[PDB]
């Protein structure tokens, strides 16, 4: 057509595919804190000159709030540029705290490195700096999380031996990150609501093994809810006696996180060193730990890292004293207790186990202590009767070890004979299985923290925390039934976190040709994932049921100061097809004040900037287009053109010359003479972003409703978290927009999307967002 | 680890034919840079923050906190990797002109395909300075100053982008505008060549092979004179000896530029009567011309100003011309004895108009037959209501940029008709025809004016002695062209050659970018939409003694004499063409690689884009290079125990014992206990040559020169060498051995296959490889 701006020739369905593809790269940021400005300048220069990385240094020559505003307003526009961004922070922790800088980093989907306590020649500091240059545009610190345990090994990218290649499972890794963030969000909910620690229990709807680890990394305990529990096939009252069949410390973590979910109080026999426990948060736990190798230092180090109360005893455990007053067990009078016995001996092992067995058969029946679970290593060459045996299981990461695990329980079999030949044949079979099938037997231990019941009918009193997705959204539950349950959950002030495929995003991705019918099919909202049937849900359906979408980014930034999960490296198209939702009562209670963790900053400009770059849209021209879209809408509503003057700038869409009104189902929009109207630009931008990734739009709209007037900043928040919004002399968050300015934006949203994407937008996506906005502003 | 789909780096899932299409598309955006010089650093920081925060533009400030050479090195090594990022980049320069001069900074800017703004020494409140600064924010990611050129005159009007009246849109004709930019650059290159060769001003004449109207303007903008060469002349169909009496049928200055640029082609000496104001002439370079200007409106300031701006020697006389005094010692025509002279007459009259014209025309009939002055051509306005006979007149022509005027133009000449009567009813019927036509066909009347500076003949037969300058493409049989080019290089002539690049075009067709409906090709014979021509390759031209140079390089090399137009968008169509200059000039003047002659604006940006897409870490990239050399040495049956692969940025491998690799430019010889670091820039230039014209041949010749340290040329600002290592002696440090270069050429095909997931072009690599082997011929 030979004109600019040009959407007609630059945006087609293949451009849209490429935008989807670019969305896998939307987390380019590293935030790197250190105390040595000349060191920062050197590695800034080295990485930008060698790899093109965009580098910023917040060094304190500008006031911290203005530096953050300038730096991250710029970065917000560049997140779809497919170039790494590194912000070095060299001001002292007194100028901007670790927790604040971490919150900002994760709100922008970045990696976070805090090394400001290091001296200039720290070998760790120099190493992490040199890693910037070596790996750019990648970096080996995860985004939005301290740790990572998937198959990607960055050192393998440097080795000729390994062909300078490594593993990359974006979808699987982002799904683990998501489980982690959802757990971290519940932990942040518990902490904000001041829930007592023994009540920090979350119900996982549908069995989902990684949550045991993520929960215990956050100091909460999981329980699984299953409709029907299959019988494992083995012996005993629950069929767990011989049922039918990359953390380096995962063998210890598998058992210990499970065992830690059964009781706030633990007898740990053979505990030294228990290094894997140092990564967990165990505030509210008490650990009585027996080992001769234990020292006073190991005790204090263990309580300092985990927050648990640790009683460290430098003795062998006394298996011959059948007293509740022996082995210091006194502390657990009138309490719950579980017992992790890790002990073993290389000689007379069969005898040692017999005496332990007799002891545990006694211990599980105490009346002054409510003993929940006891685990013991089992390796027996003879036939042996056992009482109170609930389970006899293989070790899921035991590999080819010949050892089983026995679990004692009040509700076990009263008596059973364990034939050594059957166990030996069982271990023959188990050790002969692939590593995966071995690992997937952890489902046998998790049976013991699974409840049977219909999640739709569960008791939601007392602020109960629940995490639910497929087991609620699958075809077997009607949408009508799920939405009533959710509406009732929000009514009860429960915390059911709900996730589901987003109907209109998925239909869009198929429409432009990204997703093939071979991979995923849908009929209306009924979805068939290839390699099960699911119901998609939309934002307006859920808002009517009292639920507000929140992004994974927002959840982890919100949870940043309690978060202890994993991060991620790549974004994933498949995960982006899903949306997550939290109850409106919690949003109104705690999220109407938009600090950076709760803001759409990392989505509100990067798609617009990408499209302006592609389509040759100058900065001012963009605002002229917005004026022109408002002009066309006002004419379509038969407003006399003499009543308004289109300006089309960034601060003035139009000026009102004489009073007029536009009819609208959320109360007539009213424009008074001699006023300037500045419609809400961020609504238009979020409606574009909502075509490609999960959207913070509904949460943003609720904050926009709240922000018709100045609002005092919350007292207990660091005010630097509000850097991205204007604050008044009086110290209040300054008003944003009138309801007229928001709803007018909602009214032209469809025309704006048609403009920006060359009429290849999704009318259905815009429509569901418009409905939700209209309900937000309902009169 | 078997499925590469779940491994990084990853080329198998990330690079398909559609990825290749998108790289072609991104090349249209490969000129993001603005260089803005101003003397006020807080002002620069304000607009840096504003453009960065609002549009994401990447901003640098060179403020003199760091030494200028290191600052240029840090800023432009960074920028070089980012040129395909599709985000605007702005370098603010606030040091003084004595730290980095205007001409140097302009050279660097244009080498990186940037716009250049010089506004240092303007006051902090200058309205022009503020306006241009505000334009950065308003227009980002676009900018309204052209790239690689001060001026622009095409359909794009940036102010229309801010107008609700104009729907906030404007015209965008990338190919047409980039073709005009290219004509302008080629002219500028020839003007730079004349200056470096110290050609006498009056010999600064270029032959344009094939009629090409815009070159008259571009040549006069650069103080050089055009002549066209055509195989055949269609008969003008008019009266007079040559048929030029009545032939058959966005510069605001264009009406006056049209005649005056032509007239300035005929003679280094001009008598201009009725000259005031002559504003349009201030845009020309006229050094070596002489202008005797007669007008009562002329003052002392006007003469001083015209000489300042054009460089011409200007003698302005505040009288009316004495048209009645038929003496060469009258109107100061004294100064023109034994000289060539043309006359431009703009004097009109409202009363006694025909009477005034017969007064002049009887003076020009006397002047045109002189003998102590060589009078070449005289132009005057023609508007006669009754019949006049006239002597010594070659052409009576209409004004091509005459919209609907009644007046015409008459040109006197020695070889014009001796006597001819001009009847009023003929010319009245003629002008009614002229007024009737569209303006598009009206302006094309230029062809009759341009006949007077056209010679007929076979361009391949032309006399090439004397360093003769020629611009030649389409109007220039493949074997015959290459022989003539070969002979032109042997003769040390300056024939500048351009042609479609066979293998780039074939690649663009094969991945699906350009359709068989727009451009067809059979081997190297191309059918455009209809006309046909041959594609040429870089090895074919090197064999004929010619070296590819890019348009970017030509304009940066010529920056200190350039006075042409810039551009805004790059163009896929134009990028299908390559331009070439004779090897003798390359060896004489281009073997020392300052930034203007460097591949810096293409050697990194494609590699970086691919590494971002394909998840290739910086150090992993050098490991891949080591692996590629490992695979190559084994396929040559070199025993692995003779070398040890390192694969870092500075050591590809270590030689354990002496070995040799057979090579047509070799053997390649490797001595025990030495480190080998192959040329990385050869590999990345080979990728870049898939998509745009290539500096690879010029680079290779410079690389051959750089096997040892080389002292910098003394007449050049040393800051132009910022991008390469310079010794404390003041020498350009050596780069690579011939082994390290040729090893890279040897693995180049496997490198392209790796980076592009086997969707590269073996023929592009092959023609580059063959040309490099010829550069390094033993």
Image: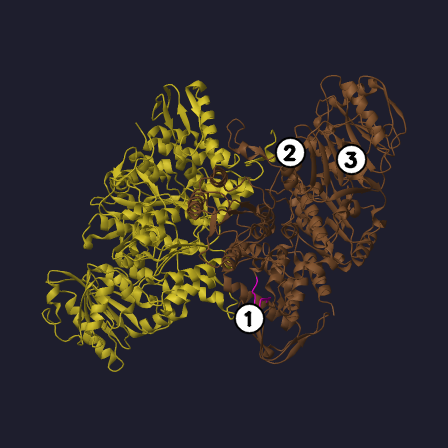
Chain colours: A brown, B yellow
Which residue is located at x 41 percent, y 39 percent?
A: B685
Q: Nearer the viewer, mark 1 or mark 3?
A: 3
- As rendered, which of B735 and A368 lies closer to the eye? A368
x, y (%) of residue B378?
Answer: 21, 66
State the image quarter where residue A665 is shown: bottom right
Let me know if residue A468 appears in the view.
no
Let me know if residue A595 appears in the view.
yes
What is the magenta segment's predominant secondary structure?
A: loop
The numbered disc on residue A329 is: 3
The numbered disc on residue B462 is: none
Is B479 magenta? The answer is no
Q: Which residues are magenta?
A: A725-733
Badge 3: chain ID: A
| Residue marked by disc 2 | A275
Q: CA distance from mark 2 to mark 3?
A: 24 Å
| Residue marked by disc 1 | A652
x, y (%) of residue A465?
Answer: 76, 50
**Tag 3's secondary structure?**
helix
Sequence order check, earlier mark of 1 and 3: 3
Q: Is residue A446 left or right of residue B226?
A: right
Q: Are marks 2 and 1 on the same chain?
A: yes
């Amino acid at each position: 057509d030979y004109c600019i701006p040009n959407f007609s020739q630059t945006v087609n369905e293949r451009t849209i595919i490429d935008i989807f593809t670019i969305c896998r790269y939307r987390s380019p940021l590293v935030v790197f804190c250190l105390s040595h400005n000349e060191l920062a300048k050197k590695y800034a220069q080295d990485v930008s000159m060698s790899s093109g990385t965009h580098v910023h240094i917040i060094d304190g020559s500008v006031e911290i709030t203005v530096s953050l505003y300038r730096t991250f307003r710029t970065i917000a526009t560049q997140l779809l540029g497919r170039m790494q961004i590194v912000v070095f922070v060299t001001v002292d922790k007194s100028v901007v705290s670790t927790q604040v800088m971490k919150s900002i980093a994760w709100a922008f989907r970045g990696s976070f490195v805090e090394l400001r306590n290091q001296s200039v020649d720290s070998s760790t500091l120099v190493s992490k700096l040199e890693n910037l240059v070596s790996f750019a545009p990648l970096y080996n610190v995860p985004k939005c999380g301290p740790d990572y345990y998937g198959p990607t090994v960055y050192s393998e990218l440097l080795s000729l031996a390994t062909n300078a290649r490594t593993h990359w499972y974006a979808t699987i890794d982002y799904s683990m990150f998501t489980r982690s963030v959802l757990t971290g969000f519940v932990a942040k909910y518990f902490n904000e609501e001041a829930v007592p620690i023994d009540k920090r229990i979350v119900s996982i709807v549908g069995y989902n093994p990684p949550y045991v680890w993520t929960c215990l990394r956050h100091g909460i305990r999981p329980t699984y809810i299953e409709k029907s529990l299959p019988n494992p096939g083995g012996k005993g009252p629950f069929g767990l006696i011989l049922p039918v069949i990359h953390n380096p410390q995962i063998k210890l973590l598998c058992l210990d996180t499970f065992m830690l979910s059964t009781s706030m109080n633990i007898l740990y026999i053979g505990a030294y060193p228990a290094t894997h426990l140092l990564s967990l948060q165990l505030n509210g736990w008490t650990i009585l730990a027996f080992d001769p190798k234990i020292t006073s230092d190991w005790t204090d180090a263990m309580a300092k890292a985990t927050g648990a109360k640790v009683i460290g005893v430098s003795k062998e455990f006394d298996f011959k004293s059948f007293s509740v007053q022996a082995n210091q067990l006194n502390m657990f009078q009138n309490s719950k207790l579980s017992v992790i016995d890790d002990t073993w001996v290389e000689t007379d092992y069969e005898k040692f186990q017999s005496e332990k067995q007799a002891y545990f058969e006694w211990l599980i029946d105490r009346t002054s202590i409510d003993v929940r679970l006891i685990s013991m290593k089992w390796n027996r060459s003879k036939d042996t009767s056992v009482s109170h045996l609930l389970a006899l299981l293989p070790q899921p990461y035991g590999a080819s070890i010949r050892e089983m695990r026995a679990f004692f329980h009040k509700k076990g079999a009263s008596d059973i004979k364990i034939l050594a030949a059957e166990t030996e044949k069982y271990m023959d079979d188990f050790t002969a299985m692939s590593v995966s099938d071995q690992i997937n037997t952890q489902k046998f231990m998790h049976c013991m923290i699974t409840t049977v019941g219909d999640a739709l009918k569960m008791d939601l009193d007392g602020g109960r925390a629940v995490i639910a997705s497929y087991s609620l959204s699958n075809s077997s539950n009607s949408k009508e039934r799920v939405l009533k349950f959710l509406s009732d959950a929000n009514k009860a002030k429960a915390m059911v976190v709900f996730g589901a495929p987003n109907t209109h995003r998925l239909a869009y991705a198929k429409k432009v040709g990204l997703v093939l019918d071979s991979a995923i099919k849908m009929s209306k909202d009924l979805i068939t994932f290839s390699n099960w049937r699911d119901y998609g849900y939309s934002q307006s359906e859920l808002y009517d049921a009292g639920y507000v979408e929140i992004t994974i980014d927002q959840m982890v930034a919100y949870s940043s100061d309690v978060y202890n999960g994993v991060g991620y490296f790549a974004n994933s198209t498949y995960n982006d097809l899903f949306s997550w939702y939290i109850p409106k009562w919690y949003v109104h209670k705690r999220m109407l004040m938009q600090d950076i963790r709760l803001s759409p900053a990392a989505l509100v400009k990067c798609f617009t900037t990408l499209i302006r770059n592609i389509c040759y849209v100058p900065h001012e021209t963009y605002y002229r287009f917005r004026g022109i879209l408002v002009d066309k809408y006002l004419r379509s509503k038969n407003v006399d053109p003499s009543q308004y003057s289109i300006v089309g700038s960034g601060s003035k869409t139009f000026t009102v010359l004489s009073h007029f009104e536009v009819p609208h189902e959320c109360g007539p929009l009213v424009f008074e003479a001699s006023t300037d109207v500045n419609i809400s630009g961020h609504l238009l931008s979020l409606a574009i972003a909502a075509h490609f990734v999960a959207s913070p739009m509904i949460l943003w709209a609720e904050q926009m409703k709240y922000m018709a007037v100045d609002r005092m900043l919350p007292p207990n928040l660091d005010k630097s978290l509000f850097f991205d919004n204007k604050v008044t002399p009086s110290g209040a968050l300054q008003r944003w927009h009138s309801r007229e300015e928001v709803l007018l934006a909602a009214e032209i949203c469809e025309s704006y999307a048609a403009m920006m994407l060359n009429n290849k937008h999704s009318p259905d996506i815009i429509g569901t967002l418009k409905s939700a906005i209209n309900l937000v502003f309902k009169i």
